[PDB]
Each structure stands twice: as structure tokens, then as C-alpha cells.
Image (tube, rainbow over all chains, first blue to last red; front, side, top):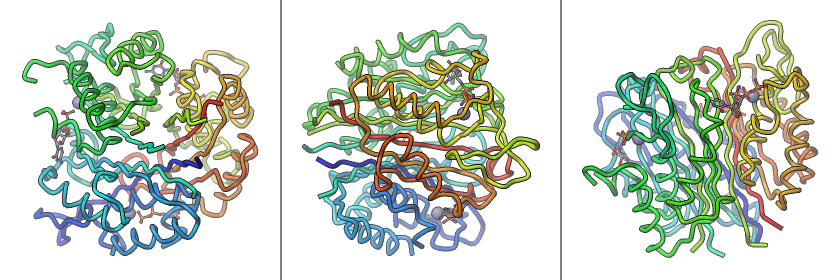
Length: 149
Length: 150
Length: 160
Ligand SMILES: Nc1ccn([C@@H]2O[C@H](COP(=O)(O)OP(=O)(O)OP(=O)(O)O)[C@@H](O)[C@H]2O)c(=O)n1
Ligand SMILES: Nc1ccn([C@@H]2O[C@H](COP(=O)(O)OP(=O)(O)O)[C@@H](O)[C@H]2O)c(=O)n1
Ligand SMILES: Nc1ccn([C@@H]2O[C@H](COP(=O)(O)OP(=O)(O)O)[C@@H](O)[C@H]2O)c(=O)n1
Ligand SMILES: [Zn+2]
Ligand SMILES: [Zn+2]
Ligand SMILES: [Zn+2]
């Protein structure tokens, strides 16, 4: 009965000499995301959306990115919540992400102890507009539903 | 009950020589989007998201299908997976033109296409305060959220 | 009862000299503040839009139009409270609110709990059903240059 929603946002810069790691999947690319972790922009957005839904603050109040997402899952359960579903969008002009998506999903499902059909990941270009459109960064948006058991 | 949430995003460049079609409604304007219906794309993505069926690109690579047909085909696929739609909410970010006059039309299109009571569909509008490409009239963005139940 | 609905909201405002910085109803010590017709509380407007959105009552402009002079310098908390009242009058109880503020500066952490408390008070909710998150934009874009602050919101309600 006690449903809650959460929403998450992250962005990271694309820089030289860094691997591109999105949703736990390493992707061949001439740049990668800049950050104090592996800078996995998708997993940060989902992490914030889960903390948001459980009213536990945000990632920076709490903290590689899969370990952090697993810890997030732990704290959400610690607070009395179970995760019903996650959905997300990755905004990246390049590279193409569609062939890596089911893998990201599998990664996320494992990390949150959820079946595949409750996790979703989607991708969009930014039509060459703004910093996203010139490939200067990548954005992720997330939504999460939990229930307080 | 087994509720699920989905979220959607889209953006399109704003240029002359195309008509402005948002939420299935053609809007008097000197420019249009490169139908490129940013609102219906966002919502479609939100619905596939809630059902966990990937995204609009994965379903529709439909050669001469407008975004309303795509939206209708989206809804049918969501139904087939066991999910009934509960509501949709959305925001259009457009520095111009004025969209308020067109909102009831957009909601009527969407509610028709999703087979929903009008009071379960909402569309909102915002400017970008002259900031960025949106605030300079170089593009328009849509955001959407959908709740479904299986 | 099980008639749940979701809403989402978005707002942005320019950051300029000579205005008070008010986010989540908290006045933040800062050499700049948000520009708008009301007090420009970007976070509260985003949450307000999300609530109207969940209830299918249109948007903040429909209810409290910037073409109306009475909302000049309007207290966005009073606006949030009227929004919640109209949402309740449409038949909805609010279950939770989540949100994100994106700003290069100032540091918002020391003010976040107070924002959450204001919102909880205005929505007549306990603290554990309201969340506020803060993000930098990693130095990217007009947000990264400090030209504005953006807020995003999500709300879940139930028709009683
Ligand atoms: N393309 C647009 C832009 C906005 N609006 C209407 O104008 C209202 C106000 O838009 P906006 O100026 O972006 O809102 P705020 O900036 O939050 O207002 P304020 O400055 O008072 O905070 C919206 O809610 C909407 O009803 C519209 O119909 N079409
Ligand atoms: N203007 C801001 C922005 C973020 N923050 C805090 O900083 C943390 C996140 O910062 P960030 O966006 O740099 O996170 P990363 O993307 O670097 O992981 C959160 O805990 C926020 O509450 C803040 O206090 N003030
Ligand atoms: N980096 C990306 C971007 C998009 N895509 C796919 O491409 C589709 C269309 O994206 P787009 O940005 O061209 O969207 P529209 O131009 O159709 O609005 C998405 O729905 C995804 O399926 C991808 O696989 N990888
Ligand atoms: Zn991050
Ligand atoms: Zn599109
Ligand atoms: Zn505002």
C-alpha cells in the first residue's frame, strides 16, 4: 500500500584517457566519463532515484559504481523498502548504445536483486544540441518505484 | 498491486520549413521541429519504460507512421504485456510560441490514443528563461512520466 | 485507495545580482539570487508543477499566472500551500515528493534539511515522505557556468 517514487539525474564530462563505463558495461570509445569513481552516470542516476524514493537524501550524503549501487540497495532495504521497478534514459550523442542495453539491464537487475522485467534502460541522442550534442558529456535520468513493507 | 513507473525524454531542433507539431497538434509558427512530435515521443518512451520493453527506437526503426500511430501502437504493446495505464504527466519546454491555448487539444489527442479518461492525462508548459539552446529558441524539449499497473 | 497517480515537474531561473537566493523557502546567504516574477523559488515551483501534474490540474501558470500582478514577489510557499489545497479539493492525498536541485554554487547541503522541513510543513506531510537532492552539473553548460539553477520534482498522490 505504501508506494513512493524517486527520480534521479546525473551528468559527467567526456575526457581523454578514460574508459567509457555505462550501466556497468565498458564501451569502446575515444573518451570516457570524468569522476571520482568509475563515473558511471547511469548507475549514479538510478542510485539517487532509489535514495530519493526512500527519502534517504542523495548519493553525496552517503558516498566502483556497482558496489555503490549495491550499497544503496542495502540502505533502501535497511529503511524498510523493497524496490518495485526502475526505468532510465541515457542521453549520449555517441557512441551507439542499443547493443549494450540488455547487458546494462542485467547488471542493474543483479545489483538490485530484481528480475529483468522490472529494470529498464533507454537511450537518446541530443540532436547535436548543447554540451550533450557536441559530445562533451553524457546525461542519465532515472525513475524508481519502491514500497514500504 | 503491481504498479510500475516510466519516464521519457526527447528534444528536437527548431527550424524554418517544417510545421510545429506537438502532442498531435499543428501550432501556428514560423518554424517547426526536425512529424518530430517531441511530446508524443517522450510519452511513448515513458510507457515502454514502465512496461520494461526497452525504448521507442527499439520498437520502431512504420515508414510513413506519424507519432500518434506510434503512440497507439505503443499502448497496444503495453496492454499485451499485462499493464493497464493509470496516468501520464508531461512538460514541454519551449521558449516560444505560447502553448497554453493548445493544451486541451494535446490532452485530447493523447487520451484518445491511450484510451484514457481525460483526467488521467496532463500536459504542462515551461520556458527556459532565455538560458541555453532551449531559451534561444533553437530547440524544444519534452519530459514525461507514466504510471501503469499489471 | 489504489487510485495512484504520478506527476513530474521542471523549473529553471537565472541567477543574478541584487536578488535574494530563496530555494525550498530557505533564504541562502549568497551574493546572487534567482530572477523571476514571484520570489523565484525554483525548487518549490518544480514541486508545485509535479503536484498539479499528478492531479491532472494543468500547470503552475494556469493557476497562478505571471501576467497577474498580485503574484509579484509572491511567497512560493503560499503558492505551494494553495496548490496542495486544490489537489486535496480534487480528491487527492499526497504520498511522497522527491526532488533534485542542480546548482554549481553555493553549497546546498547545509540548507537541505530545512528545505525538506518547509515542504513537509506546506504539504502537511511527515519528514520521511519528502526528499530533496542537490547536484552540481559537473561544470557543464549554463548550469555549470552558474547562470541559473534548475530543479526537478516527482510526486506520488492517491485519489481518496
Ligand atoms: N511555451 C510556453 C511557456 C510557458 N507557458 C505558460 O507560462 C507559464 C509560466 O512559464 P514560466 O515563465 O517558464 O514559469 P516560471 O518561470 O516558473 O514563472 P516565475 O518567473 O514567476 O517563477 C507556464 O507554467 C505555462 O502555463 C506556455 O503556455 N507556453
Ligand atoms: N550546489 C550543490 C551541489 C551539490 N551539493 C552536494 O554534493 C553532492 C553531489 O555532488 P556532485 O553533483 O558533484 O556529485 P558527483 O556527480 O561528483 O558524484 C550531494 O550530496 C549534494 O547534496 C551541494 O551541497 N551543493
Ligand atoms: N546513443 C544512442 C542514442 C540512441 N539510440 C537509439 O536510437 C533511438 C532514437 O534516438 P534519437 O535521439 O535519434 O531519437 P529521435 O530522433 O527519434 O527523436 C533511441 O530510441 C534508441 O533506441 C542508441 O541506441 N544509442
Ligand atoms: Zn555521478
Ligand atoms: Zn523525437
Ligand atoms: Zn519558477
